[PDB]
Length: 155
RNA sequence: AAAUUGAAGAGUUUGAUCAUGGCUCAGAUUGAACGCUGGCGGCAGGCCUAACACAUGCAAGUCGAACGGUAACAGGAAGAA
Image (tube, rainbow, N blue to C red; front, side):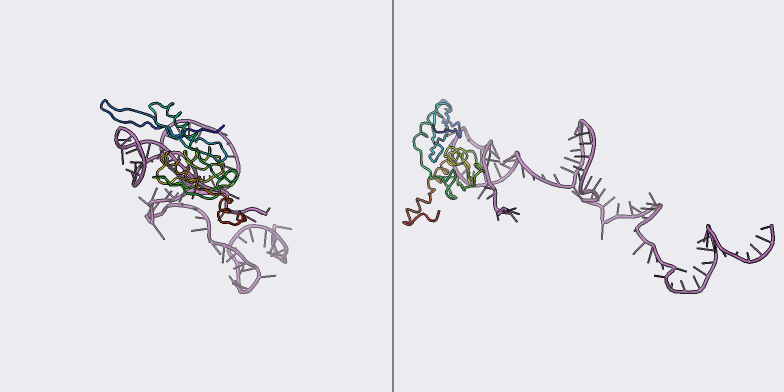
């Protein structure tokens, strides 16, 4: 019972001897809403087939996120090719302050309160890749506590 | 007790892509102006330009418990109706 969200549909084209060959690419994201989120990207000669391929690729290739009561553990920075992403944990009641692709990722991921901002290029594919890379690199107090070989009294 | 609890993007270069990069938009705000329209009230605001020139009226008077006074109006007055 995971939530699936179509982020962007784009029409690309390859040229051949006869003319242009138009195909469609769809970027989606799925997530169970409590710390697991994955994005899929499918190209197809039609829009519904592209969305189906994106959903199948997104249902696999899902990552785990260490949430903290529905928000981030700490401010994180995600970077892909052109997009640099900043996410920050907020208090209860603020919502998701983020762009379209960031909103989709953080909403299907299970994040409820976050202050986010996208720098550089706002390309949807690179934005969702940067968001996923920033969320999977976010660690919890138990992780750092066990990695430091000392109790979790820092929490 | 409270008195920083706060951060959104989109369109456009290409047959298509990523990046760079500028232009434009979505938000607030104003001593505002113009166009169409216009019922009431409360609170505020109202020459941003020519520190250009000014008709007219007012905007700095007051004290007789400082003084010599009596010109005006109100009285007291002696004497002539």
